[PDB]
Image 1 (cartoon, rainbow, N blue to C red):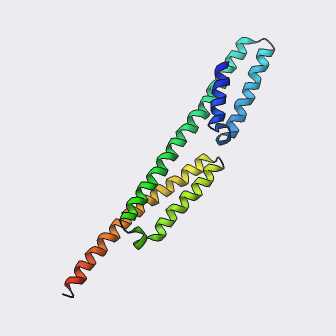
Image 2 (cartoon, rainbow, N blue to C red; image 1 turned 45 degrees about the horizontal axis):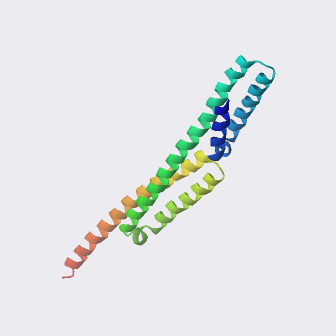
Length: 157
């Protein structure tokens, strides 16, 4: 029963209750029922309900943590591929592709800040895809330009 206090407080610290408001409300109602059983001195029934209260809180914690990991991975790797795109003249050849990545990352962060985790993950993923596409297109445009000047040079001299 002190386990539940400890798990529920950790969940609050990670804002699990705001990312998963419907499921947190459900787990609080189940916690209330558990208390009532103990009040009415039904300790078998109470203990049976306490194991599910525990498990429900542990699920919000684990899912919150796993989605945060994925968000971190997507944000760090968007950055890495924009860097690589920019080393390949992305601001010369495809500046509006770089803007679209940055704007998808901006719109993903607002969703994340209104505690809408799955839609934030959806849009960070869409920004990561366009980051990869941008890096590739920038390499291709750079190689092509280079090639078309080594030919323009040789058809002048």
